[PDB]
Each structure stands twice: as structure tokens, then as C-alpha cells.
Amino acid sequence: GKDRTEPVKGFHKAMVKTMSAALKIPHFGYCDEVDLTELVKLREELKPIAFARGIKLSFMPFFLKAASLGLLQFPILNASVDENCQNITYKASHNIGIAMDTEQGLIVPNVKNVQIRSIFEIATELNRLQKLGSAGQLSTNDLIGGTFTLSNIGSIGGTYAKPVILPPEVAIGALGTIKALPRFNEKGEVCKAQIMNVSWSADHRIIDGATVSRFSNLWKSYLENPAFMLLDLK
Amino acid sequence: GKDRTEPVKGFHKAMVKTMSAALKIPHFGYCDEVDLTELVKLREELKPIAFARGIKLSFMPFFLKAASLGLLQFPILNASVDENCQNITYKASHNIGIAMDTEQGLIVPNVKNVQIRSIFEIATELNRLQKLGSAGQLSTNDLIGGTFTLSNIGSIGGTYAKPVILPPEVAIGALGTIKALPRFNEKGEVCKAQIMNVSWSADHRIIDGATVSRFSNLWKSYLENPAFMLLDLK
Amino acid sequence: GKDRTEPVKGFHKAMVKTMSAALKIPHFGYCDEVDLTELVKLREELKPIAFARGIKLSFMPFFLKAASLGLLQFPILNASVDENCQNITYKASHNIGIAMDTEQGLIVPNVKNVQIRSIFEIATELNRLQKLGSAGQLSTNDLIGGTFTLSNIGSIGGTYAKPVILPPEVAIGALGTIKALPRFNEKGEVCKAQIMNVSWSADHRIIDGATVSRFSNLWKSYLENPAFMLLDLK
Amino acid sequence: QGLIVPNVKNVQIRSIFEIATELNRLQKLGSAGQLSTNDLIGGTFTLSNIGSIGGTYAKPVILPPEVAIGALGTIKALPRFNEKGEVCKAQIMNVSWSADHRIIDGATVSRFSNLWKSYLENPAFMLLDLK
Ligand SMILES: CC(C)(COP(=O)(O)OP(=O)(O)OC[C@H]1O[C@@H](n2cnc3c(N)ncnc32)[C@H](O)[C@@H]1OP(=O)(O)O)[C@@H](O)C(=O)NCCC(=O)NCCSO
Ligand SMILES: [Cl-]
Ligand SMILES: [Cl-]
Ligand SMILES: [Cl-]
Ligand SMILES: [Cl-]
């Protein structure tokens, strides 16, 4: 009915600072679609094992394990850059951020050392972070040390996106809604395919188009063909 | 023929100033597709009535009314921030800008108080703004006071886009070309769907992903299910 | 399993500088899908004439010639602006850059004077630039004078992208992976269509949405209907 | 107690949803015998939903000093032709208007009924002008 001016205060002040700092990063965008038909089936077969263990298993633990496997081949995506992009710190831990918005705005807790965790341990840790997130009881150690982020915008809606990189990280992916679409198979028959879009932003001062693209193709081959993941897990 | 250097002058200076000011806004992109099969059919039913009343009825009056209804639920999308983004002004009037290009460049008049205007009054005012716009006759009061912008790039071409936010607004949507695509219905049969893409940009210092995504899903439910709009209009 | 700090040095310094200068450009993005079914067929028929002449003929020569044709109608897209964007230099030569990542190296050699070259001459020069490109032997003259850029990300992967404009240029296009998708023909029958995505970025200080979109529609008509190119070539 | 005719105030500035809200409120009070004076007075036009129980057509009695009343019959599925000429399931409802013919002529009641019916047969017609 009438205009109203309000302070930006509290835990809101941090998104202002974080996003302002991201203006120093020249964002390159690269996007793709990934055929999740096989993963959808896989997850349905694994759901009762996870539920029998008291864990909810979404698609995120798969996306995270695949990003970790890709980041081992393209370690420059799990790196940080200094004040005027003069030196690159290759970071060994894959502490991968889960962007969540609470009844308080943006919170980005991370799963620590994804590289040494099984898909099941990741699911476990995701459930612990969601439980604390929704309670507003995430601790400092859950929030610091992030090295890469994924934003599952599709748990709510969307296709493509242009996510903003979280300084001092150099990359972020946004995942869209998994949707059944008509797609051709090998024999050229119109089939039901479970398609998801992915939108990557990368700091183009240090990350070139080919690196993000090859990383993305690798992440994508692991999800399209989850058996590729098996080959090198211990 | 040979290189020719040339002053940017007169009205062309304003887009330079406007777009350069937009560099201060950390843009977040969120996109989606909307199924407009039912709206396309509905617009065909209404076309003859609007025509009898001397109005061209396009899709815009629908997009605008659905945007207004969505903004009632997500009022922070119809708001401004100050230089530092220290304070937010929630703006009560939905003065929704219509980006148009003329030979002197970018011109964004707005429809005042969309929230108390019907789809037919919105179409009338759009028609008035287009005529004036093309004749170079927009008033100062047609141009000032905008609180939110839509850009129908799809009147010319395109699917997705990354629109630039117009300070001091915090969000803008770009609408792509409505195109027929093969999509599944609930029976799981390949049907002819009229699909349109939407691309929202939002000032990420104060707007998080969930807000823009929930707003978008609401706008989109009103357009996919126009019955939804009827429930709360008077 | 330890972090490692490493200087950015050598030809890695140049991408930092270029991409940081690009932060001063307010990027507008505009995207589309192009139906390349006829072109895929056309290239297949020319491929054997190309081989006989000792030339590999990809899609890029077609993309390059159609861009040069559109740039003739929309010369503002082949222009540069100054520091504070007070003067436009319309550049006569179409020196179209081909963004390449080597092992080096974001490197962007260009095809000089595309406006006076046949598709086969463009393919010849592309082959030369690819040969020297992969040997790290591209010369200074191959690298300078660029006026517009295309980035074939789809040689590796992708659908849409957000490419970064290369100062002092005002536009860049990124081309996604050509992929067969079910699409309707005029009869409303589900056909196999070779679809490619294009993502344009343009300096919205001097380039409006209508210009990039009409240019894109023109480029796209030339590729969807390659007969249109025949009419006006000499 | 027999006949009770509360009314919804100023329908012209109310949404379908606010009208539903007021109907529920009036139904609830009506059935507790708790309708207020204000609920009961000021009526300008009346509808009687006979079809909540049964019926097709009816002859409703106008309520002085109003000039018109409509009675709504039971909605039911009847075989009807589409525009192709195929036999379709159609949900058919009858409406019966009574109007004071000293001042309301037949063209007025018919034209009003045709407009009322257009809005219900084609609901998007309501979308056009609601705010
Ligand atoms: C915290 C979290 C990432 C966790 O996501 P998650 O691990 O998928 O868990 P969830 O939300 O409980 O998922 C529940 C259901 O949604 C489904 N789902 C999740 N992501 C999906 C996607 N991209 N597409 C389709 N379905 C999805 C899951 O399959 C699950 O389905 P069932 O209940 O049928 O098994 C998510 O809830 C969230 O907050 N994401 C929002 C991202 C965001 O807000 N980013 C904005 C950008 S800037 O502020
Ligand atoms: Cl940028
Ligand atoms: Cl940004
Ligand atoms: Cl910008
Ligand atoms: Cl598609």
C-alpha cells in the first residue's frame, strides 16, 4: 500500500559483502544438458538401502562424488586466486559447498574432503548439514574452508542459471530441474529421457573455456554412465 | 569501406550511463521454460473481444499481470537499494517497465500500478506506450518511477538471454520466442507444446536464488494455469 | 594431499589482463537455437571437394562467412569503443577471431578480411591457423587486428554459454555442440533435427537488444537456409 | 425456521476467493441460526441454488423490493454435440430467471442471462476485465 525503507541488517549483511566481492571476478559461463535416465534408475534401486540405514539419498551425493572425481583431473577448478590474480593456490581437500537459502538467506556449508568419502558418507554428511541448516544451527566449521560449490537450484525449479562464484573459490555449478523430455536413442527412436541442465561459472582470469568444458564432460560421463565411477573407487 | 570513428551523442549517452551503473550490481541469472499451450489457446479466445474494443491483445498483458501477482508474494523483487546496499526500499506500486528499442536506442516506459489494472487495461496502456514510443512522444512521467522490468526479446528472436538490471531496480526478466516443441503429456505421449523460455537477472546482494526461483514458479503457474489468476482478481 | 601456491606467469599473465579489462564492459547476453539440418547435409556434400583440395572443411567457415554477412548489415557489432565509451570506431575489415585454448594459452588468432573471402578460402586460413596454433607457432600478425570473435566451445561440449567480450571488441558468440533432437516439421511430424545453440555477448553501452537479435536472426537464416548466402555472393 | 436470505455485500469489489470465504461464513452462521441483521438486510438481487438438492428448471419468487431472482438447477452430464458434430459429455446446468415485468423487459433479462452464461461457459472472459 505504501513504500517502506528498511535496513539491510544481521545475517543479510554477509550476502551483500560476498556478492560485491564477486564483482572482481570475470565470470565465464558454460552450460550443458546431462542425461540422468540411468542415474534416476540407479538411485531408485539404492533408496531402500539408504533408507534401511536411516539416510535419505538424493541426487546430490552423486553430483558431489562426480565433481570430486572431475576435480582430481582438473585441479585448477578447486583452487583460489590472490588479490590481483597473481598466484594460484591449488587446494588438496575437496570441501564442496552446498548453497542453501534458509529463512535467513544464503548459507553455504560444505562437505569436507569429498575426495576420501563414499557416496554413502556424503549422503550421511548432507543429511547432517540439512538438519542443522533447517534448524539454523550450522557451526563455523561447517561453513569455512569451502573450495568449490554446487547450487541445486532445481530442488525448487529452473533450467539454466548464471550462478555467482563465491570468492576465493574459482568455480560454481548450478543444477536445474530433472525433467522427462523426448530424446533420440541409438536406434533413432524417440524415448523418454531424464534430462538435467548444468550451468557452470568459472573465473576466466585463470580458467579457460576448454578446462571447464572438459571438466564438465567428465563430470557428465560419470553421471550418464555411473559405472565409470566404479572403475577407480577403492 | 575504411575505419570511421564517431561520437556517441544525444540520447545514445543515456544507455552508456545506465549500463555502466549496472556494473555495480552482482547479477544472478535463473532461467526456466514455461508451457504456454493453454495461454496461446486462451489468447485466441480473447483476441476477438479485445479487437472489437480496438485493442491488440498480445501475450505481454498476461506476462505483466502474472508478474504483478507474483510480486505481491515476493515484494523484495519490486524494491530498490542504495549505493552501499545498506537499505532496501520496498516499493508499493508495480510500475512495470517495458524495454523497447527505438532508433535513438533504449527506452523503458512503464505501466503504472499494474496491481490494480486488469489484463485489458494493461493491453490498452501497452498499446498507448508502443504508439508514443515509436513516435518519440513518451512523457517524462511514462519513463520515470519504474520498479521492475520485462523485456520481450522474443518479439524478435531468442531463447534464453542475460538481461541487464536497470538501477535502481533489483530484477528484470527476458522472454524468448514462443515455439512449438515435442513434449510429453501426463499420459506420456509426445504432444505439441507451445514452449517459451524465461531468463531472470536479480541483484544478488539482496535477492537469493530461492526467492527468484519461487517467484518464477509462481509467475509460471499463473501462465501455465490461467485459471489460477481468476481466483484472486476482483 | 597438500595445498600448493604457484605463480601465474608467462603467457598466463595475458588472460588475467584481458579478462580483467572485460569487467568494464556491461555484457548483455542473447541466446538462440539454430537448426543446422540443411548445413550438416550441405557440408557432407562439400567435404569430398574439400578433401580433394587438401583442406579439412568444418562448420566454422560457414559460421564465419554468415557472421561477416550479418556484420555488413549491423556494422556496430564490428566496432570498438574508447575508455569512457564516448566514441565508436566502426571497423571496415572483418577480422574474425577464433578463440583457441592450446597448452599455452587462451589464444585468439583471426581470419583477416572475411568479407572478401570465399567459404573455401576461410577454411584454408582456418586450417593454417589450426596448424600453427597446435604447434605454438602462431605469429604476431595472426593475433592482432581482431574485430569480432567466435568461440566454438561445441568442438568439446556444451549447449549455451556466457562468453566474455575481448576488449576492445564489442561482441562475441559461443557455439554449442550440434546434436540431433526431436523437432516438428511444417507438417507437425516429429523429425530428426540437427540443433546447435548460439550464445552472443555484446557491450550494452552501445549495442541494444534489438541489434544483437536481428543480427542473430540474419546469421541464423543464412545457416538454416544456405541458399540465402548464394544470392548475394560474387 | 424456513426461508433465510443473507447476502454477500459489494460482490463487485470481491474476488471469487473472497466471495467463497463470505459464503462459508454465511453458511456457518445460517446453520447455527446466528446470522446478524447486517447479513440479512440490503440485498439487491438474489440467487437460489435449488440444485444443491435437485431439480432442473424452476419458477423462483422475486423478493420485494428486488426486481429479479435466478434459480440454479442440478449440474449433470448429458450427451451434447461439439463443434465437430461428435457426441460429447457435457456438464449441463439449467438456470431459471424471474424478473418484475412492469420495469424489466424480456430483452434485458435475456441479454443479461446471455452475458452471465458467456462468463461461465468461457471463464477466461472473466480473466479479461478482473483486477
Ligand atoms: C540443501 C539442498 C541442496 C539439498 O538438495 P537435495 O540433497 O536434493 O535434498 P532435497 O531438497 O531433500 O530433495 C528432495 C526431493 O527433491 C528431489 N530433487 C532434488 N534436486 C532435484 C533436481 N535438480 N531436479 C529434480 N528433482 C530434484 C529429490 O529427488 C528428492 O526427491 P524424492 O523426495 O522423490 O526422493 C536443497 O534442498 C537446497 O536448499 N537447494 C537450493 C539451492 C539454492 O537455493 N540455490 C540458489 C542460488 S543463490 O541463493
Ligand atoms: Cl564479465
Ligand atoms: Cl557478477
Ligand atoms: Cl552486467
Ligand atoms: Cl529442447
Image (spheres, coloured by chain):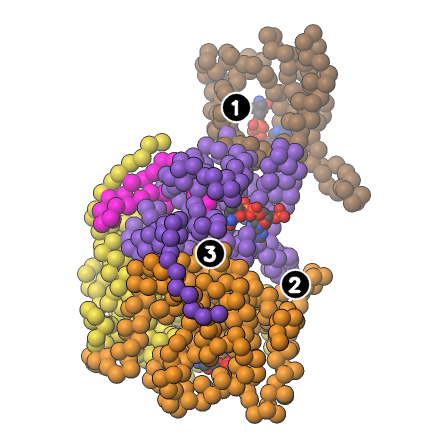
Chain colours: A yellow, B purple, C orange, D brown
User: Badge 3 is on which residue?
Assistant: C209
Determine the secondary structure under disc 2.
Answer: strand
- Please determine whether, in this image, residue C33 is positioned above or below residue D48: below
Q: Is residue B94 visible?
A: no
Left/right placement of residue C57 relative to residue B166 reads right
Q: Indicate which disc, 3 or 2, sits on the residue closer to the N terminus.
A: 2
For disc 3, the chain is C
Q: Label 2 is placed on what type of residue?
A: Phe
How dense is the environment of label 1, judged by Cα within 10 Å: few (below 14), some, or many (20 and up)? few
Q: Residue at position x 52%, y 81% from top?
A: C122
Residue B127 rendering spot, x and y as whole percentages: 54, 39
Residues marked 1 and 2, same chain: no
Residues marked 1 and 3, same chain: no
User: Badge 2 is on which residue?
Assistant: C184
Q: Is residue B97 magenta?
A: yes
Residue B81 rendering spot, x and y as whole percentages: 28, 46
Which label number is shown at residue D12?
Answer: 1
Marks 1/2: CA distance? 46 Å
Q: Residue at position x 36%, y 31% from top?
A: A1
Residue C51 rendering spot, x and y as whole percentages: 59, 90
Q: Is residue B190 visible?
A: yes
- Please determine whether, in this image, residue A127 is positioned above or below residue D69: below
Q: Which residues are magenta?
A: B77-99
Q: Label 1 is placed on what type of residue?
A: Gln
How dense is the environment of label 3, judged by Cα within 10 Å: few (below 14), some, or many (20 and up)? many
Q: Label 3 is placed on what type of residue?
A: Gly
Q: Is residue B112 magenta?
A: no
Between residue A137 and residue C80, name the one nearer to us: C80
Which label number is shown at residue B160?
Answer: none
